[PDB]
Amino acid sequence: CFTNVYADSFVIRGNEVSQIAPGQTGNIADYNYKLPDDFTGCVIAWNS
Amino acid sequence: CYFPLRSYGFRPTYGVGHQPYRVVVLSFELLHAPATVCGPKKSTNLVK
């Protein structure tokens, strides 16, 4: 069970799928969206 | 389906808390059987 469930969503290029992961640096993770080292959570994606 | 394997992101500057520790666990049983591993202590003579 969880207290504080938050859900996040946007569009990326397959080049940038690895950049969503904690500690990874690259101009999307530098300037658009990044997440903390103890991130208690999961990434999910598909082509669109 | 995941074959249960992963690899720690062991990097030099990155890991704090999420850092590698080398662990050694010593296990033993004592005062319940013959003994072969023993403290530095020296025997006395035996008096009856």
Image (tube, coloured by chain):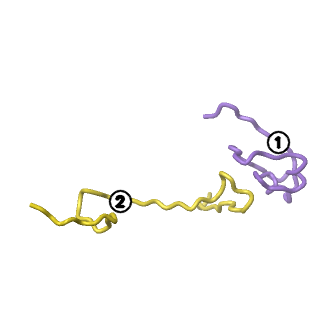
Chain colours: A purple, B yellow
**Vertically, is B2 above or below A38?**
below
Single out the residue that lies furthest toward the left: B48
Type of amino acid under label 1: Ser
* Percent coordinates x, y for residue B41 in the rendering: 31, 64
| Label 1 crowd (10 A; few <14 / some 14-19 / many >=20) | few
Which residue lies at the image location 87% right of the left edge and 56% below the top edge? A26
Residue A40 location, quadrant? top right
Residue tagged by mark 1?
A: A9
Which residue occupies the foreground of this view, B1 or A4?
A4
Label 2 Cα crowd, 10 Å radius (few <14 / some 14-19 / many 20+): few
Quadrant of image for the N terminus of chain B: bottom right
Q: Residue at x 39, y 59 (%)?
A: B27
| Secondary structure beneath label 1 | loop
**Left or right relative to A46: residue B3:** left
* Residue position for label 2: B28
Q: Given the image, what chain letter belongs to the residue carrying mark 1?
A: A
Task: Describe residue B26's horizontal placement relative to residue B19 as left or right.
Answer: left
Q: Residue furthest bottom?
A: B36
Q: At 89% across and 46% down in the image, what residue appears?
A: A32
The residues tagged by marks 2 and 1 sit, at their Cα atoms, a distance apart of 53 Å
Give percent across and percent down for residue A35. 78, 45
Q: Is residue A14 left or right of residue B16?
A: right
Residue visible at 32% across and 67% down in the picture: B37
Seen from the viewer's position, the closer of residues B35 and A47 is: B35
Nearer to me, B16 or B8: B16
Expressed as whole percent of the image width and height from the top left, the position of residue A44 reads 75, 49
Disc 2 to disc 1: CB gap under 8 Å: no
Give the residue type at disc 2.
Phe
**Chain letter of disc 2 in the image:** B
| SS at mark 2 in the image | loop
